[PDB]
Length: 78
DNA sequence: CTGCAGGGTTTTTGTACAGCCAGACAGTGGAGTACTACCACTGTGTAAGACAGGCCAGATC
Image 1 (cartoon, rainbow, N blue to C red):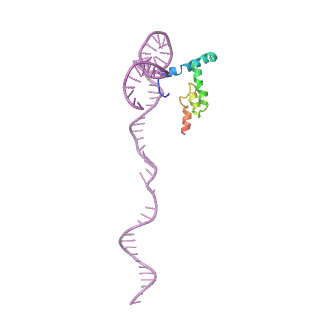
Image 2 (spheres, chains in turn green, brown):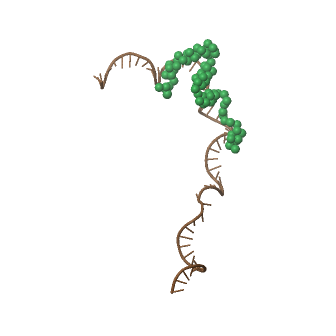
Image 3 (cartoon, helix red, strand yellow):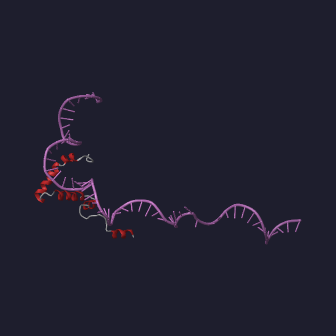
């Protein structure tokens, strides 16, 4: 039941998946694992995501937050 | 049918080579950090009813 096992079982559960992903990256996008695996979530979730899919996906390195400028906080408070 | 027992199945759980990045450690000098205490003072308490005395007005002989 895929809830809490460690790395070295999912390893061979998805060896073929990651080999195919690397093959596709080498064929079409050069082989950048990060850019492929970050975008994999977009369409797989977006078939049926509520709205939080987009938030947690844009929660990437960009943005970012550290928090709002103190002026915006002051405006919220007053 | 039950019970246990060699081994199978596939799957885990971990140790194994071996190279290498990410963040903690020490420190510093002090800053600005961030979190606490101290200080007087607030709000929600919120209306009729019982009893004693004085007196007056209407009924009676």
